[PDB]
Image: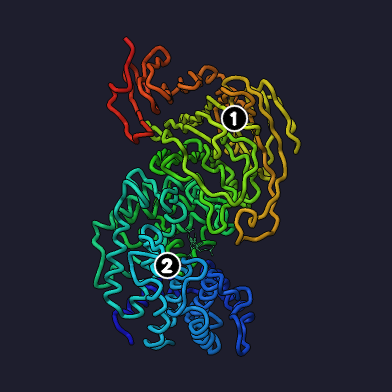
Amino acid sequence: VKDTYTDRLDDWNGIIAGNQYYDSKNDQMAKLNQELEGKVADSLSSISSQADRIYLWEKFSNYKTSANLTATYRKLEEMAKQVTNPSSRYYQDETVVRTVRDSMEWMHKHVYNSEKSIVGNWWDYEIGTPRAINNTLSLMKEYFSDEEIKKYTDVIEKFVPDPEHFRKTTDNPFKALGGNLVDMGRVKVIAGLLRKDDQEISSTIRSIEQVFKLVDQGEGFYQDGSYIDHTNVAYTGAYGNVLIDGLSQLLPVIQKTKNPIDKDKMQTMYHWIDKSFAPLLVNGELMDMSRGRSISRANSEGHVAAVEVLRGIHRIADMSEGETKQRLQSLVKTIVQSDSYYDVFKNLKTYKDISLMQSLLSDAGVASVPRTSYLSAFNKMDKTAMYNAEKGFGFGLSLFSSRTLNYEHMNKENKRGWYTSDGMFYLYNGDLSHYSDGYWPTVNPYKMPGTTETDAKRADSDTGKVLPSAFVGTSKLDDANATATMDFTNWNQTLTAHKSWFMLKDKIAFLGSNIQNTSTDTAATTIDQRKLESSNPYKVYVNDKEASLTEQEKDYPETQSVFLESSDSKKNIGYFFFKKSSISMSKALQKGAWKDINEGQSDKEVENEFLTISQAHKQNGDSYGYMLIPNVDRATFNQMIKELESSLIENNETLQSVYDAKQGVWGIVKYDDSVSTISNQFQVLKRGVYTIRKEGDEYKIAYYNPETQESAPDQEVFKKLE
Ligand SMILES: CC(=O)N[C@@H]1[C@@H](O[C@@H]2OC(C(=O)O)=C[C@H](O)[C@H]2O)[C@@H](O)[C@@H](COS(=O)(=O)O)O[C@H]1O
């Protein structure tokens, strides 16, 4: 029956598919249409048309595997999209209409109904499938009776009757929050509209409002921009994605129901965008350190994942007004145009999303100015993101502590992320494809960049762990300078190291001290493991003399510097060792398959060439110290290392500090409360992290105690001499 409920469903259809905006003369849209045409065509030619079939699609036949249910229903949603698209060859096609109706009935009688119990993954039974069912019925509501719709959605009410909890029919339900809570809306709000159930709609919207509250513990968004999910995992880039992506779709519909959400409550959305999401986006790429186990998915590499956030932002901009709308449009525009590697349209899956992106990009009224420099210390999730606009490089520092899990391996995904948070670092430069094109299934998991580890074998069956120490954190001074440390202990408590980082605007110093090993395994710190481009080869220099790297590891004793020279300076990487160090390097083709790190992925062999730089630690009390200097040519790197000749102030078991004379900035990490005199100019008095700047006779201080997660009054930690 046509009423206010169907009106809302019409708006929903315009959002999830957008057929009403389709334009055959629009190349980007025609491209998505053809994709859907192909998908439906394939589904129609492989579906079982035999009586007494045991499945609809052979490749999704074993229904004891919950994933097959969601995949099956999603195939029906694709059909519903095309049968209602005037420009589709399947528009109002009698066979497709009957196929969708008959398929819904079959699955309802033999595979998914209220008389069933969760078998496999609860996610499919409560989120994946219900969403596919809602969208199918919503798109084809003019081909189904209200009774049939209520019939096919009853099962949704059986598995998800409570808008505040998930796994309600199991022996271990959980409180819905963040991304899941948004999906709860895409389940119960839509089902509610389909069932014309006001109570379900009102109660679900009320439950959804919890998402707008910032937290100070648990899952959710924090004031410092961090986003935690799954109890204690940094997850802005995956579950955070689902949250903004899904919520931006729902809001236009929710705000037109009899239970609209207060404007002041939704105000936090803008905080997420500016404080939580934006910093993790560099040249169109969403930083992998925030994507959890999703890094092990071939179809979700960095630039692809970024689009989920960008399209969410764009939708929010569209429902916003004036300056707020104007600036969000500019944010999306500048990020997209800075991405010369990935075509944003490849992940805009609805015509309205394509339309919005096109108008934004062609509207001269929307400014597209390169983003300025920034540095976000996401202490509540132990990650740090840095971007230098003048030089054009991004830097990501992935850590963990007693407050966060190192890596997430579940549902057979991300089997080898063991060391992705053990002081791992990311460098975002001219090569936007670096962490893409199969980086994850080909990178050597035992040598993640920046990490200090023993070479003991690791089991894929292992799961994440929290760190024994709480002494992990970043002290930020300004948009270009910050200091961080990690009181590191490896997975089996056989190795330790005081690892610290000194972010000094256009370079980052890496210092490690108190390195100890109690095992029989060899210990080493991976200085880098950079994925190469066959089109842009690097010329390697050691102590400024060209070197020839081979697959076989070569040792370089008494090394003062290493320089990776590209034809594009924005891809150059230099390493300056404060004190001559013994390192080894090699360039080798590494092979692997996505299935190796994610059971549900392809076993197709992938290959990439990598340049690995390492420093062995054969004695207790060992250390390392070097400055990472990117985006400068060879002569400029050589000049810079001369300026930094005496930048290392100290690197021992209780004190680590680097000084940038040009800036007048000090980065300092103290492991105890002894009085530390620095450069005969001042004293720092407490255990913690410092970033200090001298401006004449003045001193600007940024102190952070990572264990108590508090700063402190200046006189408690700093004292000027004389
Ligand atoms: C945040 C996350 O990893 N969520 C998991 C699901 O993944 C998301 O799926 C969708 C969607 O519209 O369904 C959008 C996102 O890009 C993607 O991250 C999914 O993996 C389900 C079930 O698993 S599967 O059978 O292995 O595919 O589990 C969620 O936790």
Residue at the spot x=37%, y=34% of the render?
A: 707
Q: What label does residue 608 carry, if any?
A: none
Q: Number of callouts in the render?
A: 2
Q: Amino acid at mark 2?
A: Thr
**79 or 199: nearer the viewer:** 199
Label 2 residue SS: loop
**359 or 679: nearer the viewer:** 679
Q: Amino acid at mark 1?
A: Thr
**The N terminus is located in which quarter?**
bottom left
Circle 2 Cα neighbour tier, 10 Å, few/some/many (<14 / 14–19 / ≥20): few
Q: Please tell me whether residue 374 is drawn above or below residue 24 in the rendered image.
A: above
**The C terminus is located in which quarter?**
top left
Identify residue for label 2.
Answer: 170
Q: Quadrant of residue 2?
A: bottom left
Residue at the spot x=37%, y=75% of the render?
A: 157
Along the horizontal axis of the image, is 651 left or right of 416? left
Identify residue for label 1.
Answer: 518
Q: What x and y, as percent, mark residue 54?
A: 60, 82
Residue at the spot x=39%, y=80% of the render?
A: 154
